[PDB]
Image 1 (cartoon, rainbow, N blue to C red):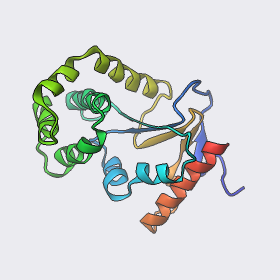
Image 2 (cartoon, rainbow, N blue to C red):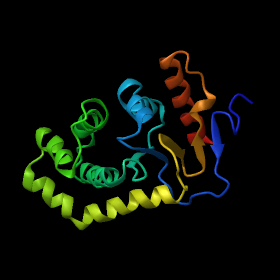
Image 3 (cartoon, rainbow, N blue to C red):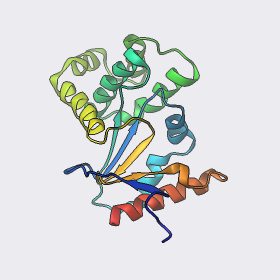
Length: 188
């Protein structure tokens, strides 16, 4: 075909029931995720081509950056709970990867404070059991596909995008292809 299992995607040999339709994994420690977010806007551009009635989910992972990586996953839970993903994503990446000013849970916090979230509001969420189970979801979803690398995207817990099987000559083209692939898997 034009879309072929093993080329623009892979099929999980044992399906994840009840998975979110579009599910993407990243790490703020992950260099390609940086590109995917700030240079390519993959998640944005996929959303632009998805049918509607499609919810898009994004989760953080623990297996990069040790003790910080976990702090970051908790922080990302906070972002989801307070609905501020859109205000912390970029400063978190640049603090980990560009400026190198995030070295502790406290520095993670600062990003949120500077992004206008209130101290007591952050600390409260940080410690809420709502965040505990949101951390738990993130780990569970990863566990359910025995995820060992990021960036990663899964369509209805049965297809996994395979980006290395797409051209990277022209960035804009890679994205389009990536998104169209997601659209195709969406409808499958």
